């Protein structure tokens, strides 16, 4: 099935793999803002990035939002964008607004590649198809509003999350057909 598409200066890719083993300018984490040590993506990123990443997260948080930015530390990225799942807001709203914020931050920081997990999936509030719709909506809106910005956006799906992979790939194929 489809795993990559180009929309003007934006390249969209779906990859089966480990988010924490990516090389990209930015890797996106997904956390409970009060405790970054739980959840499959968060635990993987924290293990790979190392203890100094948690220290910087905590220090930055104490100085203070939907995205908190740290260095990559032992990840092969320059920055980590930590999406903060604040408990008091509806999850679909957080997903949409955090995606928009991440993509704008890419322009702010001269980012050429950003790798996301299957953001917004694996909870009880958002259907996988809904998460895919939201994410693709925001990436395509971004491309329409910032046509000049060259960016590779990759969604990295855990290799055994086959249903999630199918949902993202189906959404890609639909978007590609709409655009052709």
Image (cartoon, helix red, strand yellow):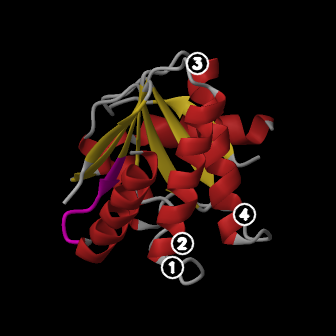
Q: Secondary structure at mark 1?
A: loop
Q: Which mark is residue 93?
A: 4
Mark 1 touching mark 4, by CB under 8 A? no
Query: How far apart, in angstroms, are the residues tagged by discs 1 and 3?
Result: 32 Å
Q: Quadrant of residue 58?
A: top right
The reply to whether the C-beta atoms of the residues labelled 3 and 2 are less than 8 Å apart is no
Are the residues at dot 1 and dot 2 in contact (C-beta closer than 8 Å)? yes
Q: Nearer the viewer, mark 3 or mark 2?
A: 2
**Nearer to me, 174 or 131:** 174
Magenta span of residues: 155-160
| Residue 4 or residue 30, whichever sits in front | 4
The residue beneath circle 2 is 130
How far, Cα to Cα, is label 1 from label 4? 14 Å
What element does badge 3 sit on? loop
Q: Quadrant of the C terminus?
A: top left
Q: CA distance from mark 4 to mark 2?
A: 12 Å
Question: Which residue bears the numbered disc 3?
Answer: 109
> Residue 175 versus residue 88: which sits nearer the camera?
175
The residue shown at (33%, 58%) is: 173
Question: Disc 1 designates what residue?
Answer: 127
Front label number (3 vs 4) = 4
Picture mark count: 4
Measure how far apart labels 1 and 2 are at the Cα level: 5 Å
Provide residue 78's location: percent of width, then percent of height: 43, 23
**Foreground mark, 4 or 2?**
2
Q: Is residue 159 magenta?
A: yes
16 sits left or right of 153 in the view: left
Identify the residue at horizontal 70%, vertical 51% (top origin).
Answer: 97
């Amino acid at each position: 099935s489809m795993n990559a598409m180009v929309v003007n200066n934006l390249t969209l890719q779906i990859v089966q793999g480990h988010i924490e083993w990516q090389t990209a300018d930015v890797i996106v984490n997904s956390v409970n803002p009060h405790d970054i040590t739980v959840g499959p993506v968060a635990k993987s990123i924290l293990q790979q990035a190392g203890v100094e990443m948690k220290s910087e997260f905590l220090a930055t948080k104490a100085k203070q939002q939907l995205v908190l930015v740290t260095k990559g530390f032992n990840l092969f990225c320059k920055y980590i964008y930590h999406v903060l799942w604040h408990s008091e807001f509806p999850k679909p709203q957080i997903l949409k607004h955090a995606m928009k914020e991440c993509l704008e931050k890419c322009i702010e920081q001269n980012i050429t590649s950003i790798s996301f997990p299957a953001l917004g999936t694996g909870n009880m509030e958002i259907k996988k198809e809904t998460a895919a719709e939201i994410l693709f909506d925001e990436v395509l809106t971004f491309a329409k509003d910032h046509v000049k910005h060259q960016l590779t956006v990759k969604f990295v799906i855990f290799p055994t999350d086959l249903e999630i992979y199918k949902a993202f790939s189906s959404e890609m194929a639909k978007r590609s057909k709409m655009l052709s």
